């Protein structure tokens, strides 16, 4: 569980519980983003978490949903995409990487979310590490737990967002 | 990552037979007995014509289709509503018809286990059902809890690769 996320009422308590679950697991920053069936309106997604506010604003401002390589990945797969240097291919994606890094978001992964009612989302989690090798060792050590977490977060958060 | 290397063979297969053999072995190696992987394309409710993989007794699968059990199987309705597992507990069989279903499934050797709902990136709807042989439900539940995180990863790997084989 999942216990607290269900007993919670309102976005504020739900966000605090999810953030703490991630933090306890070893991830300092998280974003839970969700769209309803047949929506591509990323700039109006249901968004939860503790990403820096200025970064979230810039992301929307710059239209980074069209650039961020994890977005297109999420439309095609249920498997995680790790924030590996190989995913940033274009010059725009290089800038995206640099800008996200400035915001403190360099190491992490994005778990695509695909709900029972056609919801489309992502749970992104970032880790503080001394290098990418350290980050990857940590992420591998907690991956099975994260994999369960993302589905619990999806089932709970879909109803909060749209119902 | 070494953790997920096992799951990579699911994309390295050529054809439904090899894919089925790989999936069945991963499940068997993990400690489960019988499995059924079922998948439908976007918008489909045609359970009698799903893409199905596994080692459920053939006569049972034939019976399930014939008797229209998809209409009453509580794991089916659950999968339309949720991404979370549904464990095969007496409490999920509520209607008299679902009691019949449970009795018939038990005769086919399917009593303890769980169903992982599958929801694909392209609207695919499915289930990965796995049965457990045990002396009682408590032992069965103890085993299932011990392998659940591995199974949770497996079901998504199976879905991603399975969808390509079924529809792409
Ligand atoms: O929430 C979604 O996308 C978003 C939205 Br909107 C806003 C923001 Br800010 C961030 C994301 C997802 N991207 C990341 O978190 C990320 C991934 C790799 C490197 C760096 C970052 N980062 O720092 O942002 C989303 C993605 C796919 C499908 C649906 C949604 Cl709603
Ligand atoms: O494959 C799907 O449904 C099916 C289809 Br067809 C055929 C068969 Br035989 C079995 C199922 C799923 N049911 C089970 O495996 C099950 C669950 C609990 C107790 C006993 C059993 N059982 O032994 O049958 C399915 C389910 C949800 C969404 C899509 C699909 Cl294709």
Image (cartoon, coloured by chain):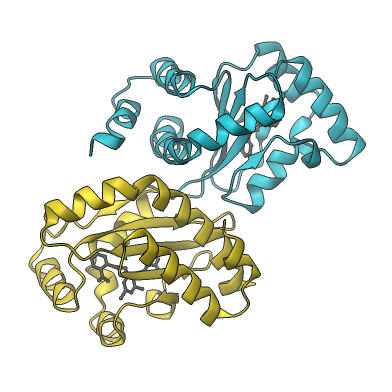
Chain colours: A yellow, B cyan
User: Residue at the spot x=50%, y=54% of the render?
Assistant: A151
Q: Position of residue B78 (x, y in %)?
A: 68, 46
User: Which quadrant would the N terminus of chain B be assigned to in this image?
Assistant: top left
How many discs mark residues in the rendered view? 0
Camera-nearest residue between A129 and A88: A129
Judged left or right of residue B95, residue A110 is left
Camera-nearest residue between B114 and A127: A127
Q: Position of residue A159 (x, y in %)?
A: 61, 68
User: Residue at the spot x=37%, y=79% of the render?
Assistant: A43
Quadrant where ligand 2 appears: top right
Whether A147 is drawn above or below B90: the answer is below
Camera-nearest residue between A41 and A134: A134
User: Which quadrant would the C terminus of chain B be assigned to in this image?
Assistant: top left
Is any part of residue A86 visible from this angle? Answer: no
Judged left or right of residue B95, residue B32 is left
User: Residue at the spot x=42%, y=23% of the render?
Assistant: B26
Q: Residue B139 falls in which quadrant of the image? A: top right
Q: Position of residue B116 (x, y in %)?
A: 57, 39
Camera-nearest residue between B101 and B147: B147
User: Residue at the spot x=40%, y=53% of the render?
Assistant: A146
Whether B99 is drawn above or below B135: the answer is below
Whether B104 is drawn above or below B86: the answer is above
Judged left or right of residue B3, residue B25 is right
Q: Residue furthest right?
A: B96
Is any part of residue A155 visible from this angle? Answer: yes
Q: Position of residue A48 (x, y in %)?
A: 44, 75
């Amino acid at each position: 569980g999942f216990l607290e996320l269900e007993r919670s009422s309102g976005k504020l308590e739900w966000s605090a519980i999810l953030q703490k679950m991630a933090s306890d697991l070893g991830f300092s920053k998280i974003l839970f983003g969700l769209l309803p069936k047949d929506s591509q309106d990323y700039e109006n997604a249901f968004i939860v978490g503790n990403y820096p506010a200025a970064w979230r604003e810039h992301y929307d401002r710059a239209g980074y949903a069209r650039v961020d390589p994890t977005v297109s990945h999420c439309t095609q797969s249920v498997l995680p995409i790790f924030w590996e240097p190989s995913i940033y291919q274009t010059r725009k994606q290089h800038e995206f990487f640099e800008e996200a890094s400035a915001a403190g978001l360099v190491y992490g992964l994005t778990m695509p979310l695909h709900g029972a009612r056609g919801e489309l989302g992502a749970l992104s989690l970032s880790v503080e590490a001394e290098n990418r090798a350290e980050a990857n060792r940590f992420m591998e050590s907690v991956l099975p737990t994260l994999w369960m977490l993302k589905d619990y977060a999806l089932q709970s958060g879909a109803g909060l967002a749209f119902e």
